[PDB]
Image: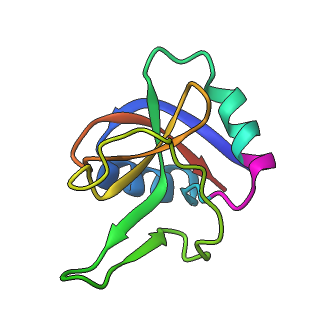
Amino acid sequence: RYLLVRSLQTFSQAWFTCRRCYRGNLVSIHNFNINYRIQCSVSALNQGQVWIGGRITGSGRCRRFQWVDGSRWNFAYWAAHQPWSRGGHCVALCTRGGYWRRAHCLRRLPFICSY
């Protein structure tokens, strides 16, 4: 069960909002079926992307890709073209096509909470 929050917020703000207002977490995606259903739900928004629960953590050369809801990173649907290196440590889903893109965490966007 997931829901869309139209309010524009930074990654950290959204993280908080999903937990306190809905007793959930920024959504995590584990298969094409769900990624597509989420895609359809936001296909009309005016913004080009929405925050989902993904984050790239770590320092140095060895890092990791995590979901704020603790589940495992076993699926991804990355956009073929996008600034990658230095492109950001937070993950967003595109309203068009449903592609995932790296984005700067302090940017304000709509987001998906699960519960």
The answer to which quarter of the image holds residue 81 is top left
Residue 44 percent across, percent down from the top left: 60, 15
4 relative position to 63: left or right: right
Q: Nearer the viewer, residue 79 or 44?
A: 79
Q: Return the residue found at the far front.
A: 80
Highlighted magenta segment, given as a residue range = 29-34
- Total numbered circles: 0
* Residue 78 drawn at (x, y percent): 53, 49
The residue positioned 76% from the left and 38% from the top of the image is 37
Q: Residue furthest right?
A: 33
Q: Is residue 52 above or below residue 60?
A: above
Vertical comparison of 20 with 56: above or below? above
Q: Is residue 70 magenta?
A: no
The structure's colour scheme is rainbow
Q: Is residue 7 above or below residue 60?
A: above
Point 32% across, 38% down: residue: 9
x then y, percent, for residue 14: 39, 48
| Residue 48, image quadrant | top left
Residue appearing at x 57%, y 52% in the figure = 22
Kindly identify the residue that appears in the image at 25 percent across and 56 percent down. Answer: 85
Task: Please state which of residues 75 and 1 is positioned toward the viewer in this rendering.
Answer: 75
Q: Position of residue 42 (x, y in %)?
A: 61, 26
Taking the image as shown, residue 105 lies to the left or right of residue 23, namely left
Looking at the image, residue 28 sits to the left or right of residue 13; the answer is right
* Quadrant placement of the C terminus: bottom right
> Residue 108: which quarter of the image?
top left
